[PDB]
Length: 100
Length: 274
Length: 12
Image (tube, rainbow over all chains, first blue to last red; front, side, top):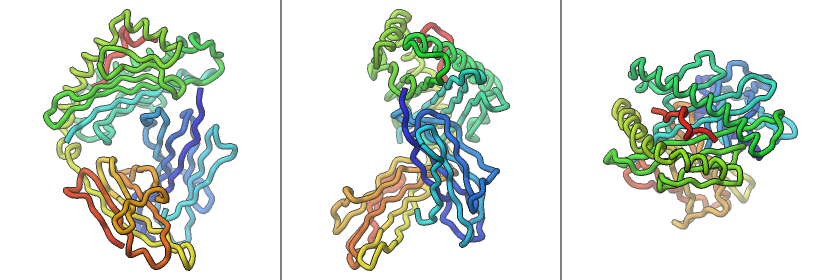
């Protein structure tokens, strides 16, 4: 039995332009076991329409999932990805930086 | 170019919960085209790319029957492995299986694979000779003896060289408009001061397909690396992929740096200069 | 097209 902590990237499908419809992605990868919680956050509140890809895995057997939601960025709204997993002592929050 | 079909299967036991959770996905190259998810309402093999929808109802009934069968065999194997390892019934455990085949530009079989994992580690794998097995530990040696006695390698070889190739060849034809395209990366380069004296240079590759790509920063032509922050290649969510490479540079010298991009959709590699 | 998981060859 093993444990691997997830890697997290938070980013948009297309280059961000305020007022223009887009997709907000959270990509979690390299984790094991497959049980994971991923929420997308809008000014700290959990976005409800959030879908994910089907569970798949890499050559080393570690899992990956894309979580995503349609959003319209603005210059003041703050977005984030909140991730929990057995290997994380507390939920981990990664803020969306339009520059990565 | 060359092409690949891969199926990925995950069974996760959830004790006292429902039956094990079972998710199966199939890809051609980096394009997903089918899924089966036991926690979905469908209980059927479902399309995930348009060119597979032209498959007739006999296809969807066979793939669905086979996916259910794979689910059932995994359920049984979960209990078997629990016994081999003397693990308690209360813990959750995972079987993962990958298999598939590669063809070259001539459509001929090039590589085939079948590998099985337990709790995130190699369990048993077909070797590249498609005739013998590698067992990762003492428990898998039990399975290896059984599979040698039941001629499993020959059955897997027949599938990998046969129906795996036949299906891959058909999918490539039926979806040539998309599977056999490349989208070259669109490259951005962005400047991010860190102090009066340093700045990050970030080289972006966006909208590219297939996913394999190499991003290198070079100072005066010499491939940086060592201090080049590189992020894992990531899906855009529209079937294309993204990646970036970042290098911290002394303020004033940015114009000496160039970003190098190699991708199969590019006739020549690119060198972009700041 | 997936493989068949119904033979003795699939049982651990």
